[PDB]
Every structure is written in structure tokens, then in C-alpha cells.
View (spheres, protein in one colour):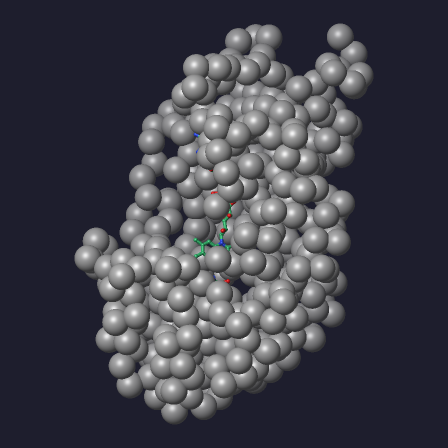
Length: 389
Ligand SMILES: Cc1cc2nc3c(=O)[nH]c(=O)nc-3n(C[C@H](O)[C@H](O)[C@H](O)COP(=O)(O)OP(=O)(O)OC[C@H]3O[C@@H](n4cnc5c(N)ncnc54)[C@H](O)[C@@H]3O)c2cc1C
Ligand SMILES: O=c1[nH]c(=O)c2[nH]c(=O)[nH]c2[nH]1
């Protein structure tokens, strides 16, 4: 009856990705007991964690993970696809000073592992795939495909971009929108024949991108973007040849990358987003992370946004036990932010990948005249609009 006492407030968190584990950690900080449920039986290339996300991780008590595994990112450059020459290059030092943290690219595998380690695998029930939630005046209940169910006071749906709970919260089923390009990504060992080990290097041209950024342990996170129709007959077996075709004529470092990579460990993903929602919560249930907002990766803010969601979620429960009031405040704080992030990503996606090839050529022109000041400013804007400023 006094809801502050241990065992009187139970949150059910669905999903053990970045969002779910962040949310559980944040809820626990605010004195709420969480049971975490995850669909897959076992976990299974990288994420750029900008300073807004880093400060969130620090706030959540998980700062050591970022310091330890974050790649040494200190500068960036854009290179011409033919010449391979610098169009613009500059250090990120100024951004790090304005935002208060260094950027931390981290391998997805390592980030996930460390966060599970931190939360503790024993407090996660795997093979638990949620199908339905229902709420009464007393609480909320969810059902799992294996026939079990669980009840609690609060439900956090952090079940990803294909969220099963999302339709119940919204009242309809949003659909994923193909963003018009395909991303190939993976990891390779740092070889300065490709690019500098402390910088994020992107080759641009023809509405395409080839990118390298350092994660931990002397490795590069790499990705290739190509504007393409969805559904092409292309997989890991067709991979090297596909990339060779798509990037014919591109500077030698790119050919070096295509030869260096391992197709068996390289991901090919057709990029989608979802039109932003105007609601994130319903009763005792809140969407968090990709479940509440699904963006293209184009400004590297997807995982950061889920961390931001969690920080705000913990904060709204810090000094209240009125679930309905807390979740309305969560929604109030998050909804405009994640809308802007999805739309910002979308716009950048469209400029980068030649939706209008002239706008794209104009962007390349701006990169030729770029000192770094305008880009740094733009990045700071995105970062400083986060909950921890
Ligand atoms: C190619 C690419 C590059 C990216 N780069 C960046 C970047 O540089 N920086 C950045 O900040 N973000 C980046 N992102 C975005 C980032 O990866 C995601 O936003 C982030 O992983 C979302 O976390 P999440 O927990 O909400 O979703 P997920 O990581 O997808 O986790 C959801 C979890 O829920 C589980 N689940 C699904 N359905 C059910 C069910 N019904 N019942 C129970 N559990 C279920 C899933 O198994 C999964 O473990 C990138 C994304 C992509 C695709
Ligand atoms: O602009 C991008 N930033 C990223 O952090 C990222 N990650 C990715 O796969 N594609 C992109 N694009």
C-alpha cells in the first residue's frame, strides 16, 4: 500500500536489447523491481554512441562500459570516391568540449554482452516471446508464446522495431517504410591502408557511401550504402561480387576493404524507418527504444535514443509512484525528441543517397567547402537536444 517498499512495485520489461536493459537499470535506480523477458534463447555489427548517449550511460551507472570498449574516435573526414582525396577533415575535439563527453563507437556484440553482464543474466528470462498485454485497474499482464504469463504494475515494451506490443499501445499497426537503400556492414582489423585508426572516414559519391570507424581492439566498423530497389536476389554468397559491381571505379582503399571483409560475417540489411507516432504510452504501458521510434541509422542516433528514453523513464519515477502520471510525463518529454530524430535521419538519408541527385551533388559541394565548423555545429545541435543536455 506504500508503494516505495521493496516488492511493492514490479515493472515487466519486454526485450533485452539496448532499450530493455537501459530501462531496467534506470527503473532499479529509482527503486523499482524489474523482471526482464527476452524472446530469443541466445543473443545475436556496431553502434556509434554519441556524447548524448554516453552521458546517459554514465548517468545509469554504466559509464565504465563506454570508457572501456568505446573506440578511439578523435576526428573525421569525407573523401572523394574517385580520387580518395580529403574533401574535408577535422578533429572532433571541439564537439567533445561543448558536449562534455567523447564519442564511443562500440561493437554491438560487446555492448550487448557488457550490458547483460551489468544487469545480470540471471535476472533475464530468455525464450519468452510476448504476444499480448492486458490491463485492469490493478495491474497489467502479458502472455508469452511458450504459454506462460507474467503480471506487474508497469509494462515497458522495448521489443524492437517489429514490436508485438506496439499495436496495443497505438490502436493500429504502423508499417515499416523502405528507405530506398541497402546497408552492408561488419568488422575488419584496422589497416592504415584503408584509413586512419582514430578517425571516422567516409568515401562519398554516386549517392553511395563507404565508411570506417574504430571500435575497440584495433578494429574498424565498416559499412557500404547503395541506393537500390528492395528485394534483390543478393545474400552472403553474392556479396563480394555485388560490392565489387556497385563500387567499380572507387578509390583503392575501397577495393582493399571489399577484399579484406568476410562475407560470412557481413550483414546485408534493407534499411527501413517508421512514420513517427504521436503517442508512446497507454495506461500502465510504455513503448521504449525501437518499439517507440524506428529510424534509419543515418545520424547514428537509434541506440542513443533508447538510452535517452531510459534515463527519462527512471527520472519520472524518482519521486512518484503514480504510474499514469509518470508515463504521461515520460511521453511528454520523449515524443517530440524521437519524432525529430526519425525525421532528421530520414532527411539526411534522402540527401546522402540521391533521392534528388542534384541536392546530393550540392551536399558534396558543401563538403568540399567545409571547414568542419558547420558539421560540428549540426552534430552539437542533435546532441544538446538530448535529456541531459
Ligand atoms: C545498421 C545499423 C546501424 C546503426 N548504427 C547506430 C549508431 O551508430 N548509433 C546509434 O545510436 N544507433 C545505431 N543504430 C540503431 C540501434 O541499433 C537501435 O536503435 C538499437 O539497437 C535499438 O535498441 P532496442 O532495445 O530498442 O531494440 P533491439 O536491439 O532490436 O532489441 C529488442 C529486443 O526485443 C526482443 N524481442 C523482439 N520481439 C519480442 C517479443 N515479442 N517478446 C519479447 N522480446 C522480443 C528482441 O529479441 C531484441 O532482443 C543502428 C541500427 C542499424 C540497423
Ligand atoms: O550516418 C551514419 N551514422 C552511423 O553511425 C551509421 N551506422 C551505419 O550502419 N550507417 C550509419 N550512417
